[PDB]
Image 1 (spheres, protein in one colour):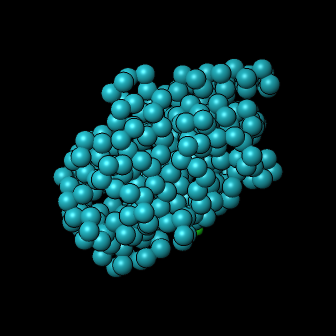
Image 2 (cartoon, protein in one colour; image 1 turned 90 degrees about the horizontal axis):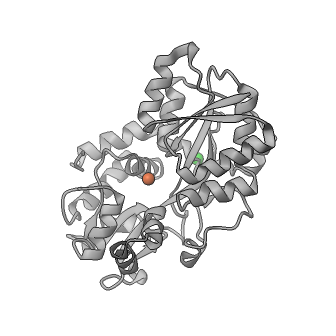
Length: 318
Ligand SMILES: [Cl-]
Ligand SMILES: [Fe+3]
């Protein structure tokens, strides 16, 4: 038999993951690619006739959007639950994280010492005026981080923070996360927010210019003396009308095996979710860090609140 994997998170090194899964289970993987938001819409439009068995994407905010679109079904698996940290899976068992990213402070090593950095909250202080680069409010990674801040602080306190943060932008939000790292290297900003794997990506790049940028920028994991760093997931779930539900479950369970954890995480320079799986060589130099235990579903639950806050404080859309 086969399973139909609808994914926005496929990298061509994941073919080795699929080939191993087939060796182990006899099931072929039929890959359907698209952007995450587009795949949700595709599955919706295909209806009860959809061939989709597994949906994979990036960011708990997108997985929550899939859940709220009605396209997932809940799965109860001892393997999933024991191996995946409770904070990285849906409380309702609709979706599950399989690799982890952190939304971190990228800093210019010449301009900023890590002793100057502490928390996300500190980024609203006036000392950072004219120094921060970050991408638009249209981006799910930002939406999820701001949702986390609303959860902690409430809308009023979070708005106060966000007004100070936005006042600190060195330029209007422009470009993607990699662009912010480049802007930090170039001195356009002294600090920026981006996902951890984008710095690792530049470190590994065969392009000399990429390696040079990466060498100018450090990565700081915020809130280590408090609640921990904001982490988010690449993940997936079994689709509501999956024609091969048993096969879909086998695939999710396979993804938490140590071999699959290594291949899948390393494919995008992300961390494993499973305890004991060694981390990528490129990530070792930055060291271990405390993760916030907040359940990542909060970042979808408060997604609309985050959009409302960002608009209220004038954080530019793309
Ligand atoms: Cl929580
Ligand atoms: Fe990304």
